[PDB]
Image (cartoon, rainbow over all chains, first blue to last red; front, side, top):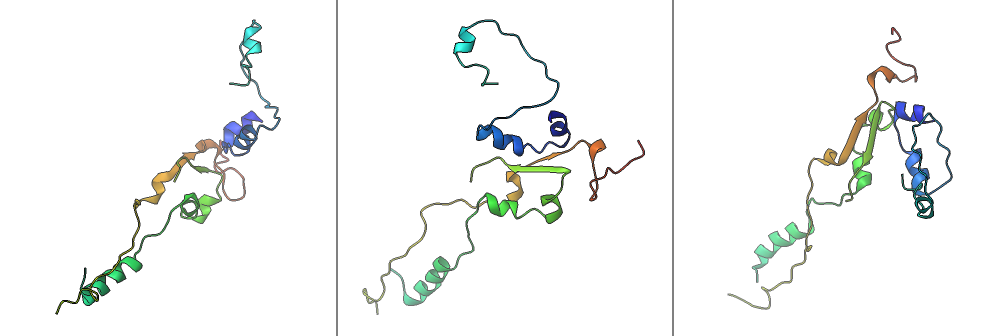
Length: 49
Length: 49
Length: 49
């Protein structure tokens, strides 16, 4: 839950899962961007953000 | 090249000195106990030692 | 009188180190928003809002 994460703000369980690259589904309303090209997909770009 | 009295004061200064090593664990055991186990306060280590 | 063999020694120490006072400067400190602050029973103080 991103909202409960924004409230307390411990960032200990999310630093663990993002350093040890475990599969995660973050839940919460989020603004995105739209990217329409293949070379920005062949370069594995979505894992950078 | 020292006198035997003058070496006695200098070997005592070399062997017995107040200086001991530091890490991130000793600093974490230095803050008081309620703040170690509080949810209102957020603390971590941001420097190598 | 000066005896050379009885008045020459071999002293031993460290190469380099650094002494740090003020241990709490290695601690990053943040605080939850004060409307969301709770007491020991994990129930919010100032229920008057």
